[PDB]
Amino acid sequence: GQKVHPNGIRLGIVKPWNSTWFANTKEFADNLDSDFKVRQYLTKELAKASVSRIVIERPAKSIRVTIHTARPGIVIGKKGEDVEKLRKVVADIAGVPAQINIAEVRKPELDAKLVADSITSQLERRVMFRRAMKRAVQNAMRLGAKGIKVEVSGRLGGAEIARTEWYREGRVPLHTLRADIDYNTSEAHTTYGVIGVKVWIFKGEI
Amino acid sequence: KDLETQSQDGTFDKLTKKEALMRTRELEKLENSLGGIKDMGGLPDALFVIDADHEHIAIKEANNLGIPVFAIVDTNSDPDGVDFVIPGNDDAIRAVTLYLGAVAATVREGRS
RNA sequence: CCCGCAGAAGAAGCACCGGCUAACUCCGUGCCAGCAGCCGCGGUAAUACGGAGGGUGCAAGCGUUAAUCGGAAUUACUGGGCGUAAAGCGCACGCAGGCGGUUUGUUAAGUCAGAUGUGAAAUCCCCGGGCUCAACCUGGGAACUGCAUCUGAUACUGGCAAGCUUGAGUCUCGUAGAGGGGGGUAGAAUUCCAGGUGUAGCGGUGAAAUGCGUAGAGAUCUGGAGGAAUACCGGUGGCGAAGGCGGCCCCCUGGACGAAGACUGACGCUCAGGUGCGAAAGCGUGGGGAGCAAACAGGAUUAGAUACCCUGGUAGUCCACGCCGUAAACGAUGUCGACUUGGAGGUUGUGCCCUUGAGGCGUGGCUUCCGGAGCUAACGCGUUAAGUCGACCGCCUGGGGAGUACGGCCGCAAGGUUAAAACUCAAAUGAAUUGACGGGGGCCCGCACAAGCGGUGGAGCAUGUGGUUUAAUUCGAUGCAACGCGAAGAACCUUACCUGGUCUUGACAUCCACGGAAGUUUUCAGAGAUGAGAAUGUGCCUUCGGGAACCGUGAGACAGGUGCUGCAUGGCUGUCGUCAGCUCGUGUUGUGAAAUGUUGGGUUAAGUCCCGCAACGAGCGCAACCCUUAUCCUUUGUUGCCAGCGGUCCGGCCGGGAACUCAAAGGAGACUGCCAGUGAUAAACUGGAGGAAGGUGGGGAUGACGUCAAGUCAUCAUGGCCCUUACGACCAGGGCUACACACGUGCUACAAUGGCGCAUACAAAGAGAAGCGACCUCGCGAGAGCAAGCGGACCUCAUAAAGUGCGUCGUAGUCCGGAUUGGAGUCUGCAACUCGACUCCAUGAAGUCGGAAUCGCUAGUAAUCGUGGAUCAGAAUGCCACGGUGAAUAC
C-alpha cells in the first residue's frame, strides 16, 4: 500500500532475526523449506497455546526450536510429555534431532502476535468489534506500554461495504529507526469473508 | 519543577551545550509564565487584578468560576465583570506602588 | 326470570413487524414480480416484494376507502407576520371611517352590581335511583354562555357646557440652500463652412480592415455659423413629499429651520373610495438637429458572430403644448407620537466667557460612520432602530401555472391597473459554516517555463499494444498513475487456448475392505496416454485372524476448478507526493453546522524556529536515529601489499618487512562550533578562517490523515454463486511468434570529433560444483579433444572498450549503413519445420539529421564507451548493477 513492514526495516539495526543460522549458497533453499515446514506445524498444534514467535537456529546440523510462548503449562502438558511428543516429528521434518526449548513471555498482552489473536479470537466468536478492539488498547496503557495502535478491516460487524477503522493511544514513531516497535499481523476468518487485524506496540524506545 | 531541578543541579551537559541551552531558554519560557505560581497546585480563591482593560480575559474566566475578584478598574473599564470594584487609576506607575503596598500590609497581617 | 339434564362437548379471527410505530429471522424471486401514507425500498446476501416461523396490536370483529375536525400557532379574536425567506401602495393631499391631550361640572348611552321576565322538553354536565352491571331509562340541580325591563353605581369611554396649556397653528426679526417656473447671458470644446501655410500620410486597433487623402487631407492660423452641455469650485456636502435638482444674472414664487416673546385655544393622527405629482424609454402636433446614438450598412473577430471591437449612421436625446403612469420608483425598511447608555465627524442657527490670539462654555435643525443594552434565523440594526409601546392604513398565506388568461376600467398606441383556475412538483427559499473551484488578489516552490545539451516522431530491426485473421492467436494491465507491463527470459516443458485421442472417486489428500514388499529388468501395439504380457525381488515386528509402509481394485463422504464478481474482502501495490501538511485532549466563542489552537511578523528545505496571541498541550508527519560515500588515527597481515635491505629465469618472483595500497572492525570528525555584519539585544540569513568535507556536505532507504468504491479472485488467502462421467484429469501436434494496418518504448544508422588494418595504455563490481574451466592441440570461425586449478582476495569466467601512435580511404548512396536473402556450418537440448542464438562465404535495401508535435537532464550529471549479474538446457538491443570519458547554461 504505502508503508513498509515495521519489523523488516528495523531487522538489521534493532530487531533480531527469527530463523538465525547459516548455510552456504547451495543448501540455502532446502533449509528454508524445512525451517518453514516446522513453523507451519507449530502453528497447527500450539495454536491453543498462545505462541508468539518460534526461533529456528541451526548450528552444526542441529535443529533448535526456541519458542517464545505465553502459556508453558499448555505447551509442556504434563512433565513435558507434549514437548517431547513434538520433539519426534519436528526432528523428523528437519531430518535431524530437535531439542525443543520453550520461552515464557513476560506479558501476554504486550506481544503484538498474541494480542492480535485475542482481537481475532473475539471476532471468531461474534463479539462487537469496537468493544473487542478498544479493550486491547486500554490494556497496553494498563500494562505500561509507551504506545499502541490497532487497525481492522473488512466486512466488520457484518457490514456489506468494507471499511477500515483504526485506533490509537500513545507515541508510535514509525519513522524513528532507533526505537523498537513490536509489530505483528493476524487474519480473522469469519462467515463474512476474512477480516484483517494489524497491531503496533511502541514497546521499545532504543 | 523537574527542569528547575535539572537546571541548578541536574543534567546540563549530557548531549551538547547547544541543546543544553535549549532547555535553559525553555526554562526561561516556563519561567516568565508559571514562575510565581508553581507552588499553588490547585485553584485560588481571590483574584486581585491591577487593570481590568488588559486583564478582562482572566476576570471573565475567574467570574466563570466560583471565585471573587478585586479589580482596580479605570474610566474605560467594565466594572460589571468585577465583584468588589475599585475605581481609580490602574496604569499609572506610582499608582500601583501605593496600591500593592496597602494590599501587601493587609495581606501580611490578614493571616491572623 | 327461575329450575333440572348432558359431555368441555357448539363457540376466534384480522392487520401489521425499515423508520414514523409496538413487534424479527430464514428461504424464494432478481430495477422482473412487486410494494407504498411519507422519506423511499427491489441491481444475484431484500428485516420494506412472495412464502414459512416467531411475534406486536385489537378482538366478534379486524383492515382499506371516503368524509369532518385535530395535530395546522401552515388564516394567528384567544394565537402569526411584512430590512434580505411570501409580504410596505412610487410619493403625497385628503372626505367618509377609526382613534384622540388635559381641568371641572354635568348626563348616564356603553360598562358594572342586584333583582325580575324569559331563555320549550330532550341532549350535555353534577348528585341520586332502577333494569344481574353497563349500554340504557330516569328524579332534583346547574347550565342554557343570550336578550328585554326596573333600580342603584359614575371610576373608564361616549353626548353637552366651561376652561387650560405642555400637542397643532399664526405673527414679528433673520439664516442657508443644484427648491420650482419664466426671460436673458458667458467661456472652453466638438462639428461644419470659407480662406492662408504645407505635405504624404490620417485615422483606428490586439493586429487590421472599412473609411478620409496628391481634386490635395491630417496638423496649424484667422473669420463665421450654429446646437447641446456646464471643467475647476464639488464636499457618505445642501434643497425637495417623491421623482429629482448643478456656470452666471433678473423676475414670480414654495418650503425648512432658529432667537425671543406675543397671540388663538385641541382647531389633532391616520385615511378605503377619490384627486394630484411621478425617472428613462415610448406617443401625438409643430420646431431644432452639434455631439452621442437604438435600427441599419460595411470591415474585422470567429467553427458560426443576426454580438462583444472599428468606420459611418436614422429614430431618439434638446424646446413648446398634450398623453403615457411604469423603475432594483431601494435606507429592498408606511405615516405620526412617546420612552431607552455612548464616541468620533460634517453642516446651518443662536445665548454666554476673553475677540483677550485660527478660540473655550451651552442649547437647537438636518445628515455620516462605529458600536452598548436589547432585538434577530443569522447577517446585522442600534436615540435618524429591525429596542420597549400606542393610533391608523396597505399587504402576505409553498414553488411553478402567473402577475398570466377572461371580463371590467383607462389608454391615440404600446400597454397599464384589477386579477384567477384547471393542471403539475415535494419542494422552493434565506442566513451562515467546511470545503472544492474562479479565464479573482497577494506570497512561495518544483527540469514547471526560461538559458542550453541531447533525443523520439521520418528508416531498418527488436519488443509490447490496439486492430485484423484464426481451430487456437490463453487470461489480466488498457488517461497522467497500461503499452521492453504480470513474464527475473512461450520449441517439448512452460500453458491456462484449439483439434484429435483417453479416465472418469480421479493428477493430488484422509478414513474403509481385501490382496500384493518397494523397487529393479525386459519386450510388444500405440502419436503418446496407456493397453498387453514375461521375469526378479518377496525387505523391517510377530495380537503372527496383520503390522508400519508404497502399489492395485471397488464403495461412499469428497478432492479439484488458471470458472465469474477486486463494486463481498484480507494481504500486497501505484499515484497525488518526499507535498508539508493531517488531526486529537482540555478549555473557550458560537442556538448550531463549526471556529480557536494550525492565524499574524519575520524565517526556513520544512505548521522548521522565535516572537505575538484565548489559547495551553500532545500525537502523526519534517529532521535526527540506519547503510553507503569524502579524511584521519588505532588494531590484524591471508590466497592482499613492496618502501627502506640482500638473491634474481629483474616475474613481488624468493627471503624478508608491516611502512604504504588494500581489506576489515572500533572510534575520531562537522555542530552555525568560532569571527565580523545585518536583523527585534530572537530565529535566521550573507561573507570569511581553519578544515578532507560548510551550512539537512553527495546518494539511498524511509511514503502521514486520506484520495482513485484505482490494480490484482491468475502468486497466495478468501465470502458468496456456479461445474462436478464436468468448466475436473492425462496425452501428441498446433497456438501464444499469426499480419492490408495503427501507436508506444528501444537498438543501429544516415558518417570524416568517421570507417578499416597493425601495435599498444588505463577499470570496478559480480558469478561459479549434474558450475566455471585456463594452459596445450585442431579449425578462418562459432566450437571440439584432453583438461590442472577453484565450491573460491590464491583458480576460472576474462584478452576491457572508448583512448593512443601510424597507415589509409576523401564527401560517394560511397571501403557509410546494415536489413533482407542463398549456401556451408557449430552448440544446446529426446527434438531447432512452424519458432533458438552464434560463426563463415556470398548478398546488399531503407536511410544524407527527419512534418504538426514532443520527452529526459542543474555535475561527475547529459551525452558517449565498454563490463557484469538475476531469469535459464539452450534463448537480450529488455531489466538490474559497475567502471572509463566528460560538457553546456541557470538574466
Image (spheres, rainbow, N blue to C red):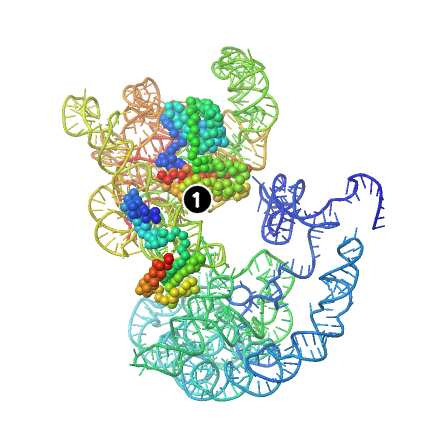
Q: Residue reaching furthest front?
A: B112
Front-most of C482 and A129?
Answer: A129
Q: Residue at x 53, y 41 (%)?
A: A128
Numbered label tally:
1
> Is disc 1 surrounded by few (<14), some (14 to 19) or many (20+) residues within 10 Å?
some
Query: Looking at numbered disc 1 in the image, what kind of residue is underneath it?
Result: Glu
Of residues C187 and C134, the one nearer the viewer is C134
Q: Which residue is mark 1?
A: A169
Above or below, comparing residue C704 to residue C109 in the picture: above
Q: Viewer-proximal residue, C384 or C472?
A: C384
User: Looking at the picture, does residue C365 appear above or below residue A154?
Assistant: below
- Percent across and percent down for residue C79 are 59, 66
Chain letter behind tag 1: A
Residue B44 seen in the figure: yes
SS category of the residue bearing label 1: strand
Which quarter of the picture shows residue C345? bottom left
Q: Where B70 sits versus C860, above or below?
A: below
**Image x and y of residue C501, in percent:** 56, 24
Residue C322 relative to residue C188: left or right: right
Position of the N terminus of chain A, as image quadrant, is top left
**Residue at 30%, 45% in the rendered image:** B10
Locate the C terminus of chain A and report the quarter of the image it occupies: top left
Q: Position of residue A120 (x, y in %)?
A: 50, 37
Front residue of B34 and C819: B34
- Residue A34 image offset from top left, x and y in percent: 43, 26
Task: Say above or below: C433 vs C173.
Answer: above
